[PDB]
Amino acid sequence: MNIFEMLRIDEGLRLKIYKDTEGYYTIGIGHLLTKSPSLNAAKSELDKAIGRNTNGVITKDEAEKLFNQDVCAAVRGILRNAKLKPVYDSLDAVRRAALINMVFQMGETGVAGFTNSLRMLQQKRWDEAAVNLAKSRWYNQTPNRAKRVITTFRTGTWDAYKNL
Amino acid sequence: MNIFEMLRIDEGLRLKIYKDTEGYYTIGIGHLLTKSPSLNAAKSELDKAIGRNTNGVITKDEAEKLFNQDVCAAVRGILRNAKLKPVYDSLDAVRRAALINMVFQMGETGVAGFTNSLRMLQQKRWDEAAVNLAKSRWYNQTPNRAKRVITTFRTGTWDAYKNL
């Protein structure tokens, strides 16, 4: 278990253009193509992203390539963020992944917004952070994934991904 | 200082197609475009990867998208490699970056062939590893960069990147 396997789980893998929850066009492992409602524009964005005319369908390897861009971009923006960075650098390897997971899902901006849970994490107050995180709109919106992310922060283990 | 800042120094950032050492067309931060002697070929690879007609020049942001791709690809490849993985998992965060740096530079296969220096690192035999690594053709080919990566494995500090 690592961040790659962990997001693949939380995000899944689709090789055809699909609509996420707010219904925008998406492919691979949670890779947003466009906010434009035109599926002709999503198919042209996609051909652009992948470097070939795909006719709406990609391979596993092409999806993993977008995924590598997205995860490292996630990590890079954590490191360039005044607020996320000292938390991330304080965290152990498993817990860093939990943090990467949240940034991947909701962006560096909304993760930098968790002022008090971030402080609890920075102070190593795992149980308080876990409780505080559970109260968020984020949790209330995707409670299955959030609870799995919060168990990772709480325990520093890969338990919430074992069985499944 | 992290793996991103460390490979930026090590590889530099070139926004225009250049020729690397085995004289292969390259752009961004050590991004290999092609092994065609042709330039319009390398220009057509670049266009494909970036998604616009570049005519051999890119932005910082474009170079960083490719860089993000290459780094996480380097990490995923460590994690999928039966010899690199347990070494990587055993290493602290600084020295992990040293291993990522090697893999970024010469690929997963050629790093997985450092049989005996890999084993020394897994056993925390830092000086012994540092000494063995300095005897490599790799070190002989790019000694400045190699010595800096070997200092990081050795000390697990960022000393070799501090005063450059």
Image (cartoon, coloured by chain):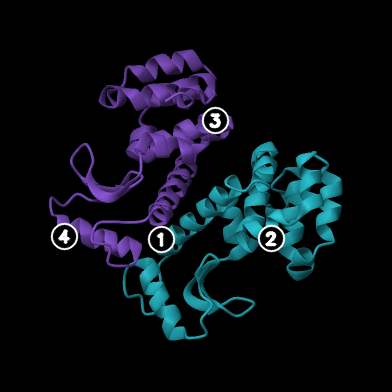
Chain colours: A cyan, B purple
The chain under label 1 reads: A
The label nearer to you, 4 versus 3, is 4
In percent of the image, x 75 and y 70: which residue is there?
A141
Q: Secondary structure at mark 3?
A: helix
Q: Position of B91 compared to A161: left or right?
A: left
Measured Cα–Cα span from mark 3 to mark 1 = 29 Å
Residue B28, x across and y down, in percent: 34, 48
CB within 8 Å, label 3 to label 2: no
Going by the numbered disc 4, the residue's amino acid type is: Asn
Going by the numbered disc 1, the residue's amino acid type is: Asp
Residue where numbered disc 1 is placed = A61
Going by the numbered disc 3, the residue's amino acid type is: Val
The label nearer to you, 2 versus 1, is 2
- Tell me which numbered mark, 4 or 3, is placed earlier along the sequence: 4
Residue where numbered disc 4 is placed = B40
Q: Secondary structure at mark 4?
A: helix
Going by the numbered disc 2, the residue's amino acid type is: Gly
Residue where numbered disc 2 is placed = A110
